Image (cartoon, coloured by chain):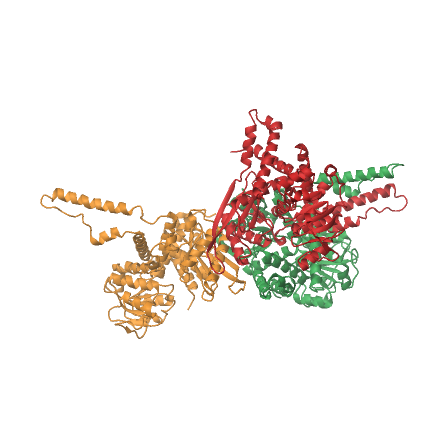
Chain colours: A green, B red, C orange
Amino acid sequence: DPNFFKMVEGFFDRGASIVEDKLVEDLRTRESEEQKRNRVRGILRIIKPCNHVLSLSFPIRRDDGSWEVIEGYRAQHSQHRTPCKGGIRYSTDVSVDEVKALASLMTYKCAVVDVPFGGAKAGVKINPKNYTDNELEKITRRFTMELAKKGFIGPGIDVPAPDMSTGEREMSWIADTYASTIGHYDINAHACVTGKPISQGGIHGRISATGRGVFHGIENFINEASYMSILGMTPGFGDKTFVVQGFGNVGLHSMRYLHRFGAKCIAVGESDGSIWNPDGIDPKELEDFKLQHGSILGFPKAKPYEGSILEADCDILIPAASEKQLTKSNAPRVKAKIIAEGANGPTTPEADKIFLERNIMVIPDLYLNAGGVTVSYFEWLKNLNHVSYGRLTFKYERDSNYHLLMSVQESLERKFGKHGGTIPIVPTAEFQDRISGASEKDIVHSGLAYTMERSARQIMRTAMKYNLGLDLRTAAYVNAIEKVFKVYNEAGVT
Amino acid sequence: DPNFFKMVEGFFDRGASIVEDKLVEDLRTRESEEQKRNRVRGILRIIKPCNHVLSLSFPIRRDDGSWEVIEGYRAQHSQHRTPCKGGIRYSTDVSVDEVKALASLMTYKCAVVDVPFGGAKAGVKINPKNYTDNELEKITRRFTMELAKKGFIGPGIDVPAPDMSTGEREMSWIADTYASTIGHYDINAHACVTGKPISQGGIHGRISATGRGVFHGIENFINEASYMSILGMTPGFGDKTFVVQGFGNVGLHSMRYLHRFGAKCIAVGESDGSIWNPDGIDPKELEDFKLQHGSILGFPKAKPYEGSILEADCDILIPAASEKQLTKSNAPRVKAKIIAEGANGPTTPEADKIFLERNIMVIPDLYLNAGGVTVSYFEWLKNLNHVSYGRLTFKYERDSNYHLLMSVQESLERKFGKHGGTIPIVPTAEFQDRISGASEKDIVHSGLAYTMERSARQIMRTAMKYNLGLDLRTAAYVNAIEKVFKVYNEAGVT
Amino acid sequence: DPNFFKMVEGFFDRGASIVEDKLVEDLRTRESEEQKRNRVRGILRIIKPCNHVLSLSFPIRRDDGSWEVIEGYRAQHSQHRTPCKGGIRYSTDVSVDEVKALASLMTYKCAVVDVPFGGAKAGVKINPKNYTDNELEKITRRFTMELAKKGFIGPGIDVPAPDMSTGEREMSWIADTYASTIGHYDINAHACVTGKPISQGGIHGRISATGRGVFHGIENFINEASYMSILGMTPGFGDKTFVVQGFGNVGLHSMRYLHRFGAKCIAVGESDGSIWNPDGIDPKELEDFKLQHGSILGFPKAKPYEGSILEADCDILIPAASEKQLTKSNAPRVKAKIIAEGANGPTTPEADKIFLERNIMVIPDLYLNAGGVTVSYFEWLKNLNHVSYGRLTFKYERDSNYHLLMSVQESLERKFGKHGGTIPIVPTAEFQDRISGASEKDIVHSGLAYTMERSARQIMRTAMKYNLGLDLRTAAYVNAIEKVFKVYNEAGVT
């Protein structure tokens, strides 16, 4: 099993060759009179590497007293985009290659969903379990101060992002550290770091967002008639059967939203055990069972599944919090029509080739897991604006709606109101509840869904343009590479 | 033919006398107990001059190698407004008076359309044709660095604007130079310079905007019944006949939009030649003919016009990219009912007096050519916000519209739905396309049209207030002078 | 042959063990009541690593046009000292370990001679010969801009230093780049980079200084009676015979100053060839012969030396611009009484052990090659002061001297001047020339000699304290480690 990093480098090279074969044909050819093959190759070679990587060896004092050094790597992929986003990870055995490849992946993920951010990644070689909470807080504070003195962390340059390992308390600590080290003089200093708690300007519904994104992404490919016909199944709006690997938060939200949309979860797969039901599993009952018991096994009115969850005859299979569980041997054996990646690199490229051979759709992880990035971008914008979304406009919109309804009322009474009185002023119960229950979370949901729909449409158009019938991952990579090429090409280079 | 600069100074003096005769009567009289004639005269004398003018003599190295100096003049008219906008021009024979008068004109143009910007102008004494692209890039970079070291260019102080001579590539170079010289640390540094390409945060539809503005401006005066009655022609919404001088981009967009609105272009005038048709000329066919041939002469189903395009019996005459083509002798000879200025100073003040004598409407250029300024201001705001307009609200608005339609559906089924089913949920085909095709360009168009309508209404009110029946240019100048007077008078002076 | 970097790490560990065995005994024991062995070990572990290392992958455009990336590594060892000095090297096959070990060596070298600077090193993976002068200038400018945006280069943080590969033209380019990128607003911005040309505030006599330092260092050990008696030779002020390996600038200045001091150079060794004379070689004649011919072979009144220059029966042997020419086998064979290192790592640690066995003195390179660092520090101070040294005081001092002489004159005439007139007012011819020829170069020479004498005295005291009879290198390393320990230990740690 090759590392994820050679995986990313190969994906970039594969997309780069295809996009280079096309750019020199249509626009780069008229861009300059001289030969453009070398010019585009040079642009691609400039795009490939990560611009900045820095290593910090900073002392810390343990609770008992050790005075030992901690090594932390910060990688900023590029400064084409000035504001960058970078997740922070506290894990043993991190490398400089770790953060370089993750920064490249992050900048491409921001590119595909049209989020104006560069890619970055911070990795601290430490085991969070071994060290106490106070020691972890001191490590975070020291790392933040050292990173700030070097001019990396900051609203203008780089915004931290919460990885699965890091909680929001760490980011409250990071925000306090930045406020102390650099100062709260600037207005934009409030938007220094994302992932903040709600009282600190934090966006609402952030935890569900990633899972929510998955629920949208699959939807955007289910609605398409062409791909569903190519696969050979009818579009499964409500009759689709899906199973999920693992019980992560993203998987939980995804299965809840799929059940709300009408889909049925015939089985749930997890490392500890698998649960099988003839028709479906209740998301709320399963969630309560998991929160109390701690394991999905033993669910009432359910029989544990025997075998491999990947090989089940489901319409959709969603691997979540999984790394290379579906191997080269697994791909021919599985009969799932659609594989939707909820985690990073759930499948091998050889398995992808096998899927292309057997005409099993793979939906790229890069498009799916960008909901959290989009919502973090929205939260950054909210922190910059310093206003809850729609605060000044909710009553204005509802007054406009009521006035429109009253206008329809008066017009109907004027024309057809000679006998009796017409009452169109009454709103729909769902619409009335939405008007009364209007909040910023609705705006965030609408923006996330709109961004996901646009990204899916652009991915489909790119796949059609380059004749990638089923290799959606390559199409997404080509789209990201084309966008980055464009920004760099027309941006002046000193 | 007097220079445009004595023209501007005389316009300012003419407006200043009229506004001074009025301010001391109504509000300045109660403002202070003592004599106010001298106080208002002092305010006007302070308003008149340009605050700052700076000359740079900076070395450049030619491709062959010459080591020769370049002289560049930067004029900021005033700092009453902190953010200023200033166009950059690369032309031989520029002067300090050049940039002073152009800065005064720019600040007045920003004032009339309620754009919160001061006036500025940069002029570099050089011939762009003689020097190669690399030499021009080096000149731009050196000029930008020298201007930045003196603290003129910057989001807070002064934002460059694209003149007809300068392309967007020069402004990409200027943005890169500013990012290098001062740094990308600030968030607002992204909004340092307007006119950026779309990938860099550039506004969409900028090229058409100026022409679009013309199409709106004339409209805002066609709809008015009082002025049309005074002229003596019926309001020509669709039966108006218009001709244009030159084939500039502004003229092209103006004639296309006029044809879409229903107006007919009986003839097209250009320096190379003129084309005459009995009824109209197709904008798309003429545009294709011009792009291929390079000259409008020889258009299919058209006969070249013999004589002077200015003297044609058109309802509307639009000079574009023209300087004093309509002289004192021309004004009595022309029979066009309306002259709409698409360029700076197309007509002489003596010709304006003759037009007032013969009751031929002149629509001031200051109000017409401000569409580009307004759109540049919108793009600056977008760069500050770092968000495409309406991104978070499009789906919310369309969901609200669908909910309103469904509410009307349910109410109609409740009242008149005893027999059959009513279907008001279906939107208009045009409305449905607009909902599906919603984008930022629509918002920019709406904002530009709203600003132009407001400016036209204020100009009409000012003209009525000061008894300027047909001298709309003087009314616009008086309005701008009054606005500037107000900002300065009630702002504290150290 | 082990790398120089394992050499430095082993030297640091060897010194650290010895200094740790002593600190816990005398001062650290009273510093804190609890156990101090672990405390001192922790301090040493914090001291060892380099705090910051950053890698830049920046694009450049070749003259033909290639658009290819350049990798450059910057290592700052620590910030215990805020102003750091770092040499810049343009050489193929540089590594991050390269710059880390060189930064550690530089900070220790600054520590031994009491120069308040931290250690740093910049290494660019490129071949200067392949690229043209314009390409090299562009590489330097791009590297400087990228390093400045990250807040490394600057008077407060890090000052560049000229390596043997880099000329002063590169540093003029670097100074211009820093002035453009950050700005000349600050007074201290003049002192951003050392190694400047004289017109730019550059110190005089910088080129000779390193060689001059060698001439002082050996002197400071020749004058000592104890070490010379231990070796078993009489102190050779004028009868000493010395030979030099290579014909570097440091070697040239060293041999010229030794000849002026009265020493005789019986033979000169170089890679191309060796020249042998019974008594001595004229430095000026040899310098002219080398500048014209390009090789020392064929010198008039000289016979080429046959054999190995290292094995010659000289009193002093000075390797210059040499790397591990004296190996383990060489050490027993050589009969030179004193080996004075003019370059970095001329000898292996095994050869050092053999020298200790055979009681042949080795004078550490760290103490010898610090003259250039000291003079660069003096030049930095001059740039900060913005005044040539002694400008306001030369005439004052000479007036004071003349007044003292006249006072002695008058007193002698009062007491012994009854008969005749006494003339003590006349100064010594050498003293009169020095008074007339007073300049800043004399002050720089005096400061360099004073610093070298103090460093030699401290090294001797440290060697006596720790019972290192002949291992002067270990004594110097222990002294540097003790100084760094002190600064860190008594400085507060967050």
Where in the figure is residue A299, as x and y percent of width and height? 74, 54
Q: Kindly tell me whether residue C477 is visible in this rendering.
A: yes
Q: Is residue A224 left or right of residue C60?
A: right
C111, A128: nearer the viewer: C111
**What is the quadrant of residue B377 in the picture?**
top right
Q: Position of residue C445 (x, y in %)?
A: 30, 54
Instruction: Using residue B12 as the reference point, say whether residue C321 is left or right of it.
Output: left
* Image mark count: 0
Residue A460: quadrant of the picture: bottom right
**The N terminus of chain A lies in quadrant:** bottom right
| Residue C469 x/y as whole percent | 31, 61
Instruction: State whether residue C210 is above or below residue A410.
Output: below
Q: Residue furthest left?
A: C419
Q: Nearer the viewer, residue B91 or C66?
A: B91
Residue drawn at 66 percent across, 37 percent down: B471
Q: Position of residue C371 (x, y in %)?
A: 34, 57
The answer to whether residue B392 shows anywhere in this view is: no
Q: Residue furthest top?
A: B33
The residue lying toward the viewer, choosing from A23 and C59, is: A23
Task: Judge by depth and name the residue closer to the eye, C214 or A281.
Answer: C214
